Image 1 (cartoon, each protein chain N blue to C red):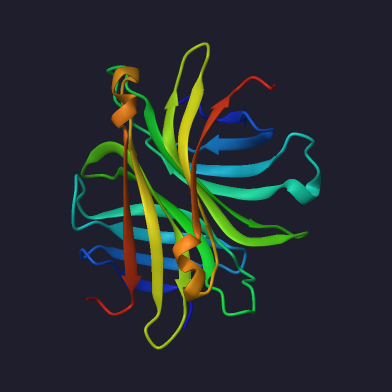
Image 2: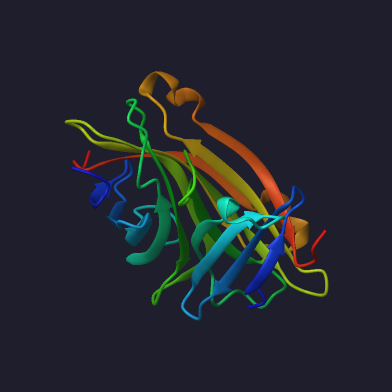
Length: 121
Length: 121
């Protein structure tokens, strides 16, 4: 039990993460949607000493959508919390910002929400 | 890439970041006064091969609000783009998620926007 492991979101993406003792998140992300192919590097942070009152564990991570196969000139950040239990879950909201000209910057950012489970839905 | 260095927002915060050749963002996020109790690890990713058509450079990073002195049980992710030139800027939107119980999860996430400059206010 814990954050370290392989997770899947509701759209079939694969989030392979390690939670280090120092609060570091590392691993790879593979998206089933969008301008993306194969695995991408992710890095992020999580609360390594969460509250003991029943609250979830806050965390966030970033993927820049460049790898050896494609470059979408964009990056997604997921912000959320880990919730333990017999059906562990990470609930997130995300922002996907593209590199744009100034005239197009107003429409540079998509917003959404992803839920991750260790059992693929 | 023009990203490595010290950046300042509109509300008295500062971060020092190194943009690695591979796409890594690493550094420290802190307050204007710069005391140790206000400093936190920052980690993220950026597009290390941006477009050459005048578009910005997509990037994102996370700070979990725990250091050796305090812990807010929360984390912010900034998603945005770097725009170069004599008045360089990092223009972001952010999500700040707190660890909560399930009953309070509906109100776990704040949203906002931050612009960063290289010039100390």
